[PDB]
Length: 289
Ligand code: HEM
Image (cartoon, rainbow, N blue to C red; front, side, top):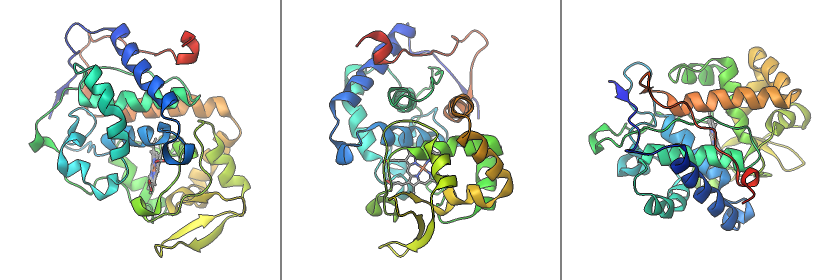
């Protein structure tokens, strides 16, 4: 399968900056969501889940087709809770009906990262909605109750290496788990993008406990939690080295996350040689808005 990026007709940087701005303004406005976390984290998770269905072997899944809009994918047990992100984006899509679904979902993630003070993430337009029969089956997103070997193997399907995996997982500085969604009991949440996932891993006194859904998770007295797959990053010696690197270099983490997240959001897409360069959107703050 080949998915060729096709620019929404006549659109350019300014059009997409307007969409970015609408998302960013709504992120600022709707501040009460999820006990005042806001919609930032769920939008990042949405962008990842619509991308993380990709399979490098046959180019099925991925962000291109915007298939999360279809019931099979929308109702994936792995996507429980993301409906909130979709509902957030609905009025945005209504205001800008010309943007494709894949472009909107991925741009939501970029906007959220940047507005939460994370790194700039270059972003490319041109995802094109594909039909319902192109929706990937459930079961392509990762389990959280597994070890480092599982994580490593899983991410090979997305063409991610050890550094890319550890960098991407840094997004777990954001938001929280919700028992009703995933069977994991949320701890201290955050809506500012930093390298504190790695600092928490290395510095907290972690205890392996069972939550009210009878699943194991790692908890600290300070009120933080880690999934078994999160904690696996300090159990595996190769992942541990990289965790230490990012814990000690905020800029390096930002740069590596930016590259890995763009790659994740672009997997499966063929960009014509004369396609526009990636866009780097200004934050509301940078615009004085
Ligand atoms: C082994 C890989 C991963 C596993 C097993 C995993 C699992 C989970 C689980 C179980 C939750 C809780 C969902 C809920 O209860 O609402 C969660 C939340 C989240 N995940 Fe991951 N995740 C992984 C990788 C990633 C990646 C690569 C990203 C983005 C780069 C990401 C971004 C997020 C964000 C931002 C949240 C917070 C959502 C919210 O607060 O509503 N995760 N993850």
